[PDB]
Image (cartoon, rainbow, N blue to C red; front, side, top):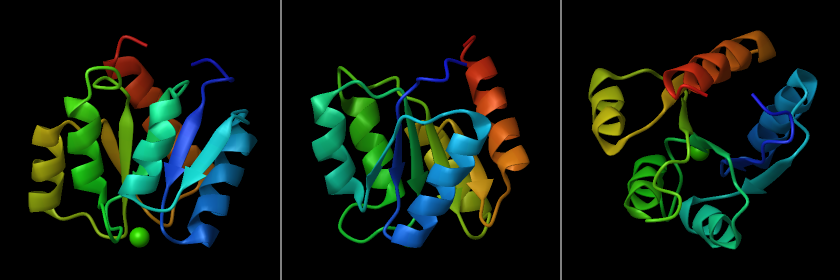
Length: 128
Ligand SMILES: [Ca+2]
């Protein structure tokens, strides 16, 4: 629950990224970087320093699930929480992501209260 925890907000809609970034700031988390797709995020995650990944399920080039599976397979970031963002809960998606290792799901649009409950729950299931 460290306020300086560095977030990576991955989403191909720049407006969605700003929303998430403002929601985060609002909660007290100001260390936020953005990525527009799976590849982009990996390029940034490489540099290190990251602590939390907020990712959109649906992205061109490298989607949310393929990004999560790549992180999880990465020796070094294999343990980064990944909160999946979707516009519609679907059981098969939730199940796919579950097995690939997603830290949770948030259905957009969402409020800061919702984003906070999500984070809190993740921070907790992680003994974090
Ligand atoms: Ca998207």
